[PDB]
Structure formats: C-alpha cells, structure tokens
Image (cartoon, grey):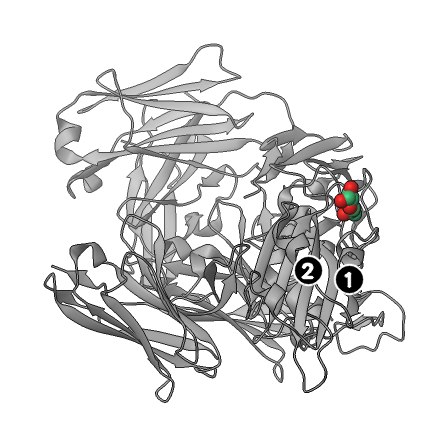
Amino acid sequence: NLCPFGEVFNATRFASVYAWNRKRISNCVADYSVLYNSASFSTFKCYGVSPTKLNDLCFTNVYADSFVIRGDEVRQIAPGQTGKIADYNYKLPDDFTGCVIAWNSNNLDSKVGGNYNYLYRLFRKSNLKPFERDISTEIYQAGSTPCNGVEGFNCYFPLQSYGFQPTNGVGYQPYRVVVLSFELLHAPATVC
Amino acid sequence: EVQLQESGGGLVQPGGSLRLSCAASGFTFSSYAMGWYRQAPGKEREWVCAISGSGGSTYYADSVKGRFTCSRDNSKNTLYLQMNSLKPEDTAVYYCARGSFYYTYGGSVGFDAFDYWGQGTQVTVS
Amino acid sequence: DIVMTQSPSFLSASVGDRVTITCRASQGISSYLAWYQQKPGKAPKLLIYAASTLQSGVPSRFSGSGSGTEFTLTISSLQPEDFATYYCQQLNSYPPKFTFGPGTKVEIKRTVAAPSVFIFPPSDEQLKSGTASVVCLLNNFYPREAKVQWKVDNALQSGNSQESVTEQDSKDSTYSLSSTLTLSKADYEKHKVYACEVTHQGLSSPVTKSFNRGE
Amino acid sequence: EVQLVESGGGLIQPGGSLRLSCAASGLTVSSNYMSWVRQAPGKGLEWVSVIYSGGSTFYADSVKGRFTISRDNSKNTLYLQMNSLRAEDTAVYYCARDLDVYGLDVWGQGTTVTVSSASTKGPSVFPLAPSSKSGGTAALGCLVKDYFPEPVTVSWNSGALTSGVHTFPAVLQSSGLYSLSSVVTVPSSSLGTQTYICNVNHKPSNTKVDKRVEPK
Ligand SMILES: *[C@@H]1O[C@H](CO)[C@@H](O)[C@H](O)[C@H]1NC(C)=O
C-alpha cells in the first residue's frame, strides 16, 4: 500500500498546536517525491537525513505531526529553539532526525472576523519535554492563592486563541506545519 | 548556563598561519555541531565553516576552502579554525556558535545557529 | 518590522468631551493591541487589552475599537484625572516582544493667551567666566505651539539655543517657555544687537524684544 | 497586596555595571512572564527584556550580549544585570508582569539609571536681573548652569514667594552638564522695596547658593 502522506497534507482541517495531531506511518512504501517538488511550502528543512536519499532509505516507522502556528513562530519548530510554541506547545529534540515542512494557510485558516478555533498554550509552569502533548485546561496559578477552578486575577485559562485575519501581516498569518520523524528500531522495518 | 569564548586573533602577515580557539561550557560539546562565522567590517557576517560533533562531517565556504581547516577536540570542549595561507580578504572578527545542520529541497546543506555572541579581538592579516 | 504610529501627538480637550485617539500599524496585527495611560512621574497604567477589552480596573468611559491596522481609544466623557499621555502597544511581535507607540498627550483646553515676552542679557558674573547666556522668557501662554527665533545683529541664529517648556499650570492651564542662547564671551562682545522674536497664535504679529550690549 | 518594588538604579560611567532588582508582592515571579521596559527622558517606552516561567529569556537587539535577566524564587525577586553600559542606556527602568494578549498589568515604580562620563559638579547661579523691559508686572529670575547630576531644588525667599514662580525643566547641554531657569513675575513697584533671593540646593555636590537678584 502507498504511504498515507496525502491524508496529512491535503487534510481539510488542521489541529491546534497544543493538541498537535500525530499519525503513525507503517506497513507502506513511501514516495517523498510528492513533497520536495512542491512550491506550496515555504519551509522544507531536514535534519539528520537528506530529502534526496529518503527514497532509498527504510525506517521501521514514520511519525507525521500536524498543527497550525503563526509565521513568526515557524522558526521555533527546529532543534534547540525557545519561545511559547517551542517551550509550551511543541518541542523538538536536539538530536532530531526528520523534516519540517511549513506552508502559508491564509486562504484556509483565516476568517474575516478572525478564526478563533486555533489555540496555543500561553501559561505553563515548566518547559515541554520533546514530543510532549499537553491538553490540560486547568486554570493557571500565577500567584500563591489557589484558583479553585475559577478565572480571575492570577488565575488564567492556559490556552489563548490566535486571531487569524486575512488582513494580518505575514508574521501574524496562519501557517500549516507538518513534522516528519523517521524512527529506526530493532524491529522489522515497515516504511521504505 | 551556556557560555562560549574565542581566542587566537591578532595581526598576521599575508600568507601566514593562525589558529583560533572556541571554548565551550554549559552543554555537552560532542552532542552539538559548532560553526565558525566572520563578521567583516562593512559587510554582513559570513559563515566560514561548521563541524559535526563527531568531526566526521565538516563543511567549508568556497572562500576559505583549501586554506582553512576546522577541527574540534571534544576532550577539551574546544573548536579550532586553522587559518593558514592567510589573505588580506580574511581580515575580520571571527565568532563561534552552536547550531544544527539542515538539508534543503535539493540536498543542499545549511547551518542554523543557536543565538549567542562573544566579544573577540579582530583577526587582521597585514 | 511593523511600525506603530499614533495620531495625534498633542490633543486639547475640556472636561466632558468625547476624545478619540488613533493608533496605526504597518501591517495587520489582528487584535494584539493594548492601551496604557501614563502621568508624569508615574508608571504606565494598563487600560485596554485585546484592543477592545477593558482591564479589570478601568472606568466604563474608556473604550477600545479596531482590528488589523487601525485602532481607536475613546473616552466618552473626559474627566480631570484623564489628562495624561496614552500609549498604544502591539503585542506578540517579532523580533521585539512588544512595540510601543509614540504616544498621544491629552491636555486641558482653554482660551488663547498671548505670552509675555522678556529678555535677560548675560550677567557680568557669568561674563567674567568666559561664557555668555542670553535668556528669552515666554510667560503664561496658550496654546503650547510657539516659535522662538534668536537674532544676533539681525542674523538669524541656529544651533546654539536650547528650549525648555513647563507643564500646564495647575491654576490657569498656561505654559511657560525659556530659550537660552549660549555663546562665548568673545563672540558675545563681537556683536551689539541681541533680539528674541516670538510667534504665537495669540500674537497678531511676531513680537521682538532686544537689547544692546553695554546697556 | 499586588506591588512591584524596584531598586538598584543610580549614576554610572560608560562601560560600567549595574544590577536592578524588582521584589514582587501578590504574584509569583517564577510563574509569570517578567519583563523589563525602559523609558528615556522625554521619550516613549521600549521593551528591554523578558523571562518566561520555564526559564526562557529574550532580549532586545540594543541590549543583547550586555544585559542579563534573572530571578530568585525564594526571594520572589526579578533581576536585571546591565553590563557594558552606554549613554543611550540612560533611562527609567520599569519591571512589569506580562500577560501576552492580556497586556502588562502590574508595573513597578521604576528606577532611574543615568550613564554619563560627566563628573558631579555644583551649579553656578547667575542673576536674571529686572530691567526697564510703572506698576506693570516685571520678571526676574536665576540661571542655574552647569550642574551634574540631577536634581536641583529652587525656592524663592526661603519659600515665602510661591505665586508666579516658574521653575523650568532642566536641559542637557553638549558638555554633559545640566542647565535650568527659575523665573518669577512681581509688581514692579516692589523692585526697589522688596528683596528677592533665589535659593538653589544641589545635594549631590553639597551645594547651597542664596543669590539676591538686583534690578540693574
Ligand atoms: C488538496 O489537493 C488538491 C489537488 O492537489 C488541491 O486542489 C487542494 O487545494 C488541496 N487542499 C489542501 C487543503 O491542501
């Protein structure tokens, strides 16, 4: 069977960065040519492997993670990076082996009044471990007073909404990001 | 607590040799790739070289190829740029940084540096 | 980079009027806009966040509107403690975390008052030190906009004068201005006529006050 | 309850070092975005630095490599270490709590940092004497020239004369010193009867000058 790569890129709706989606690519043959010869992408950066050598390489599994962020934050999807996205939403390991592909989605994820469905985690006490997904909606305690589940001063909802408007600048415009991670394990390989 | 410092610069005659050293702290030196940059006065900073933590893969700019060799001694947590067969076009302040190698659409290789800067004495070839 | 601009820079209004000030962005910043108020000698006070949401701790007369590139802060009925400087600030930017605007100063409007113009020649005490400082005083005027031109032997001076303006007076809401023309004793004694020309709204024609060295 | 108390500012030479402290009450520094924002004399506000709850730090372009943000959780105190100080860094620095879209809501009183190679100088007081140009109002005053650092305090007749007094804000001259004017308008009938003395106090130089302005 052909590898399920179109079902991640051609997807109708993308996930929020705090709840980034992961798909396990297995038991298929992969043709990465649908990717490196495409001009929709503004970022195609591969670490630990060459895109040209991917066709002749085999991995036990592949992991395709998808989310939507701001353009000014796409730089944060890279090893050894800091920021709200890299620290509290999606953290890549320093020894990352895989590719990061990002394209503009102002025609898809923007609304005239502002698309408020895409959310990012704003408040978190500690940085995210690599490939960690935090979906907690617990009220953030910014002081010594316990929140008891009610919002207010020093008691803030952890998730904030991107306002994605077509009139926004490139730095405030929505960008769809897919991160492919190639996993080689002591197991029968299923992706080639 | 990451810090990195450079040394070895000075005034040198054209055609000479000089070695610049980048000492590292706050991280495992072998784990991360390190690169050499030059900020020429009046231009933009240009990437000179970068070396993998293993040292097996080293990438050099075409300007400095065949004359400058980049080496690392992970035992001493140091990065070296062997500036030999020097030329007056090689006068600049040189900097080292941590970073990650990345491959582009066609297999081209680039070096992306983690943000940092270090005060250094200008390397002048005269 | 996205640049913040504010209009106007100086606004005059009385107590009770509806005041509207505008902030403009180079590119669309959605609703990532905040409005702060600052009084002299005091720290800024947050008034509006998300470009339309009133901070817990602002009166209802403050309101914020706008999306993208144009934003407005509106005070429906001005109050005596609202006479201050107001800053718009873009949020969640790059490279800087946030970017502040030039600021709009709201001041008390009153009747037009022409300044009283005085001139003070250098004292012999300061002369003996090798420097001469001529002083021009504009007392109790409104509005603030005023032009002061120094003249040495009918030659229009430029580059050797410094101006200082007081705040709006607590009683009559009038400004006062001082222009100091500093030069050396030699160049002071090389010339005779020293004049200060004042242009203001309340003056039908510019008013010149002069002195001759040696009384 | 909620407050940010700042300290550590002062006078420093170019290339010097300083450490500003911001003690918090009513909020946990380690659990918030903590920002330093400066304001130059007569200018607007400029973001200086920010520290995240997770430890990530970010600095403005004009201060990268010279400034360092930090915090002590036990003391609940934010710290800004300013090294390689330059004259353009002279400003009032504020510590604030950042809430991203919710804005900077809690601010400190601010601490003044002056960076100048100038030396502490006592002011020179000179008379702005009344001249010809009846009972109409006449203006007199004092010129307070070439003093550093700010501030200076000017009074008239040991505080007995407060009406009509206009003490102008100080201007920074090209020499790095400060100059200032104090004027007052009085009935011209009292020029020959009432004495007029300006009292100038500059504590940093321990200078106190009482100058009597003579019609001349
Ligand atoms: C999916 O692919 C089709 C055909 O290539 C294209 O017309 C469409 O815009 C794509 N949709 C998305 C969401 O990328």
Location of the C terminus of chain B by quadrant is bottom left
Q: Residue furthest right?
A: A149
Asked if residue D25 shows in the view, the reply is yes
User: The residue marked by circle 2 belongs to what chain?
Assistant: A
Asked if residue C37 shows in the view, the reply is no
The crowding category of the residue bearing disc 2, from other C-alpha atoms within 10 Å (few below 14, some 14 to 19, many at least 20), is some
- The secondary element bearing badge 1 is classed as loop
Q: Residue furthest top?
A: C204
Q: Which residue is mark 2?
A: A31
Answer yes or no: disc 1 within 8 Å of ligand 1: no
Image location of residue D148, percent across then percent down: 32, 55
Does residue D105 lie above or below D198 as drawn? below
User: The residue marked by circle 1 belongs to what chain?
Assistant: A
Label of residue A177 in the image: none
Q: For the residues marked 1 and 2, what is the alpha-carbon distance in whole angstroms?
A: 8 Å
Q: Is residue A160 left or right of residue B23?
A: right
Q: Is the C-beta separation of discs 1 and 2 under 8 Å?
A: yes
| Towards the viewer: D14 or D57 | D57
Q: Which residue is mark 1?
A: A2
Does residue D29 lie above or below C157 as drawn? below
What's the residue type where badge 2 is placed? Asp
- The secondary element bearing badge 2 is classed as loop
Quarter of the view holding residue B80: bottom left
The crowding category of the residue bearing disc 1, from other C-alpha atoms within 10 Å (few below 14, some 14 to 19, many at least 20), is few
Q: Are marks 1 and 2 on the same chain?
A: yes
Does residue D152 lie above or below D136 as drawn? below
Nearer the N terminus, badge 1 or badge 2? 1
Quarter of the view holding residue C156: top left
Residue drawn at x 65%, y 79% as measured from the top left:
A184
Quarter of the view holding residue C215: top left
